[PDB]
Image (cartoon, coloured by chain):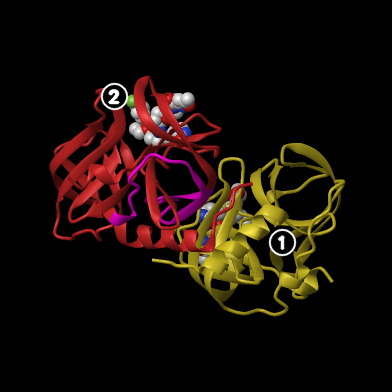
Chain colours: A red, B yellow
């Protein structure tokens, strides 16, 4: 069915090894992408509090911002600033500047149960609006793969671009929230 | 952590897309590797009967042979001949001819819940003998990855070599049965 490229697999591998951690909230375990310095991202439905477990180390959250567009609509991204010695590789230059469609993407998961899994998801479409668990959400990417709980937070990449994080699905399709350069560079 | 090469991921993807199906027995679902014609392999612990579900289509098993070496020891490979119109790409030339060690291997799964997932497992070592669920087993490959149930039948590959199928683990390590060219020729 779906296929990815060699450089695509190697690009995903480099992001996972250097820019992901296992995050655990009250709501469960999630893959977490670190973007730069001590700034990382996680789906809003994870309900981040004043503390979070990062690789099983409880870490103080210095700040969190649940992202909403100018229509005050959910984007399902929550940016968190972490009180933790280690800093992230700056990967902002891999973030897209515009909404777009993509071919042969890869979904990568980093949890305790699946500490290094890679899933080619195929063509990613700009789906736009989504009724996500009853919450209207915008800037959604869609792919036809039977995604599962525990893949939320998973990083979706193309060769050279980190395009989103997984946030939902219906049993036959997966949905990711867009990542955009403007969210982190202003 | 564990790492694989682009060519490694691309070879595994080609094997999965062309030479794997979802097999479901009374004992559960397993990844099933087709080797040539209508011949496929599955772990013996799947307890294959006279029928099997191949991609949710009940298929008549024409023959099955649970492999044991010349010491009459379990190998955990079962070769099945399937009553199935479509035939498999012959990939016998990718099978190793002898026991060996491998680097930066990949474990690939094709089940209903995880249809085509890829896991770098790192260095694969010829472990040899294993007491698998109380059954003495030979020709076992070992890799340090926390494998799980539902990854049994998963194909272990390196670029150009189909080296084994997953059959067990202990929570910190995974174990696969060797595949050898002599089994099919
Ligand atoms: C991962 C996160 C999770 O499980 O909950 C965290 C506490 C999970 C992944 C999906 C599960 C099933 N397959 C997946 O990929 N995410 C969720 O469960 C979100 C809610 C959903 O995905 C719902 N699906 C839909 O709403 C939907 C809409 C369409 C067109 O198709 N499906 C569930 C019914 C599966 C978690 C979430 C996010 C934002 C919210 F406002 C509420 C809930
Ligand atoms: C895959 C098949 C399956 O789950 O269905 C069979 C009921 C599963 C994979 C392992 C599960 C846990 N993690 C895995 O990778 N395979 C099994 O459960 C076999 C038995 C085992 O793996 C045991 N482990 C050991 O024996 C062992 C030995 C050493 C040195 O380290 N671990 C369980 C304790 C997990 C299934 C099997 C195969 C052949 C038999 F004769 C009996 C049982």
Q: Quadrant of residue A135?
A: top left
Which segment did they paint magenta? Answer: A93-120
Residue position for label 1: B77
Residue position for label 2: A73
- How far across and down, in percent of the image, does residue A136 sit? 35, 22
Q: Nearer the viewer, residue B103 or B86?
A: B86
Decide if residue B73 is on the left or right side of residue A50. Answer: right
Decide if residue A58 is on the left or right side of residue A175. Answer: left
Q: Is residue B136 visible?
A: no
- How far across and down, in percent of the image, does residue A75 sit? 31, 31
Q: In the displayed image of the protein, which residue is found farthest to the top?
A: A134
Can you tell which of label 2 and label 1 is closer to the viewer? 2
Circles 2 and 1 in contact, beta carbons < 8 Å: no
Q: Quadrant of ligand 2?
A: bottom right
Q: Quadrant of residue B76?
A: bottom right
Measure the alpha-carbon separation of dots 2 and 1.
54 Å
- Seen at 79% across and 37% down, the residue is B58
């Amino acid at each position: 069915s779906h296929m990815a490229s060699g450089p695509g697999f190697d690009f995903a591998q480099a992001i996972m090894k250097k820019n992901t951690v296992i995050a655990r909230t009250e709501k469960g375990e999630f893959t977490m992408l670190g973007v730069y310095d001590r700034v990382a991202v996680i789906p809003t439905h994870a309900s981040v509090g004043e503390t979070i477990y990062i690789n099983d180390v409880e870490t103080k959250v210095l700040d969190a911002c649940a992202l909403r567009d100018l229509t005050d609509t959910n984007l399902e991204i929550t940016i968190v600033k972490l009180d933790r010695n280690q800093k992230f590789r700056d990967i902002r230059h891999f973030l897209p500047r515009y909404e777009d469609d993509y071919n042969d993407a890869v979904l990568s998961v980093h949890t305790s149960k699946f500490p290094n899994m890679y899933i080619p998801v195929g063509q990613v479409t700009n789906y736009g609006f989504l009724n996500l668990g009853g919450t209207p959400t915008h800037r959604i990417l869609m792919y036809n793969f039977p995604t599962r709980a525990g893949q939320c937070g998973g990083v979706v990449t193309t060769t050279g671009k980190v395009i989103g994080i997984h946030v939902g699905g219906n049993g036959a399709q997966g949905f990711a929230a867009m990542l955009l350069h403007s969210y982190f560079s202003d």
